Length: 306
Length: 306
Ligand SMILES: *C(=N)[C@H](C[C@@H]1CCNC1=O)NC(=O)[C@H](CC1CCCCC1)NC(=O)[C@@H](NC(=O)C(F)(F)F)[C@@H](C)OC(C)(C)C
Ligand SMILES: *C(=N)[C@H](C[C@@H]1CCNC1=O)NC(=O)[C@H](CC1CCCCC1)NC(=O)[C@@H](NC(=O)C(F)(F)F)[C@@H](C)OC(C)(C)C
Image (cartoon, rainbow over all chains, first blue to last red):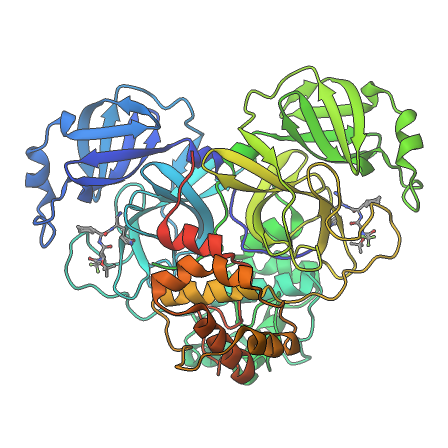
């Protein structure tokens, strides 16, 4: 019993974190086999930030311009390449602590775990969602760039995020591990805003199922509703539409609790309409949307990793 | 910017987790040097749970009754000992992934990180506080016993918690790593309840400082109040008294924000009196108390580990 924003154990990822230094700019890199991934804006200078041309910036670099620490050990870069917005620095040493790993590009709504790092040294680990506006409500200070987000699946680290920038609204923007930004953001210091965010409806539903699994049951009703009619209420309250594919993902949870999916939809409808009346679901006074149906099942059933 | 329930990276602790099996009972153990710590109720049987006498239960065991997996590798117990409520199983192999480590017994109010484990395999990592009633609002399923809680301080893992049991109210009880329960709980399957909990006042204050550091500032006032008068309002709302020693710990934060400690006390007083008016502090619709002043400074300043 109990329900926490639970992050994957971060050991597999801690042993891949390294410092990368070009000129006056120090940020984090990720070390897999004999390659170090980091945000390409490490090659920028204080005056190269307004509209940087990374292609000319990078033709002008030689390998020894890249200082890479793995701890107190000094790695040697033997070649560099740019893939979208990430630097791939081929180094002479293969990381022996490389886990089995994949690069995945995740859909808005999925969650991942973030290992926040500074100078190649992990600081902390927390759980994030990729918001519908392809930003993340993260916790990131100066020098946090290059920290990654990831999921673990038995033994494989699916890296899904690298951190690049903080937006004026305080949310965060970055890329998959092939350097494509999530969302329409660019690695330029120009005006960019986050864009209207919505609530991840299917996750709110999965969290309400977690509640039923953990003993809260006050928010239910004998009402039901159609999918069409549910979406009409959702969009008013700035929720994402719920698809039939969402309903199907929420199947196992529906069946474990005996609450039909369109029934939990009627519960949420009433919750959005009437509020929580100053009660709390799972110790939360807000409808929580950063838990996927996978997450709920991982936590309320007890899935491990090797 | 941003503020998350941030757990310490758990790599150092993942490499200490092991499975421990006596008879029909499998639970987690912690492996430091050549010793495996686990809850002593692993030697219990289904009928030995009402008022177990662990001394007679343990004189009757021989070493080979203890099956210890470190992964797919099978450890050999060469001796056993009971220290309070924990088994110390001396094994023939020293754990090579033993970090520098301390056992500390923490005061209510401190927080730690929990690595939830099943069959010796870590499942997830989240951040807990030791509540004033010496329970923890954790997330724990069957077989989670032996999972530890811990803090990291540069390179040293200060283990502070082992998990033993879930209480009827769904909160969790366990011990320090020398086997003394936090609180008045015993490892017996008899009636025990959690006891009235209070809110960790100094932490609520430190979180409000985190808010000021991260841009929220709506909850302040030109009011001030005396310590005496603040405690009078606190105890009404079931908050802990705030001591002068609390005020001093909150010094660095006071000085980083220029909000006198007794001024943030006047802010909280008004917040407890008038509510939040359906606003949110740091994305939270509740006064959050599971962040120590240390935590806020770690996260809003960026402290790392090696
Ligand atoms: C990298 N380590 C760092 C991480 C930032 C710093 C504080 N919190 C973070 O998440 N990233 C940057 O500082 C980054 C610099 C880089 C320069 C070349 C172009 C690509 C980005 N920039 C930012 O995060 C800034 N934001 C923007 O410029 C944006 F366009 F609005 F996104 C950031 C410094 O600006 C404020 C002050 C946070 C609004
Ligand atoms: C150990 N792996 C396990 C972890 C529990 C199971 C589910 N969530 C957890 O945190 N611990 C126990 O099941 C433990 C068994 C042990 C037996 C000998 C005496 C010491 C404890 N017992 C409990 O957590 C039970 N609680 C109690 O008996 C208590 F006295 F109220 F604390 C638990 C199984 O009881 C309910 C059903 C959770 C109320």
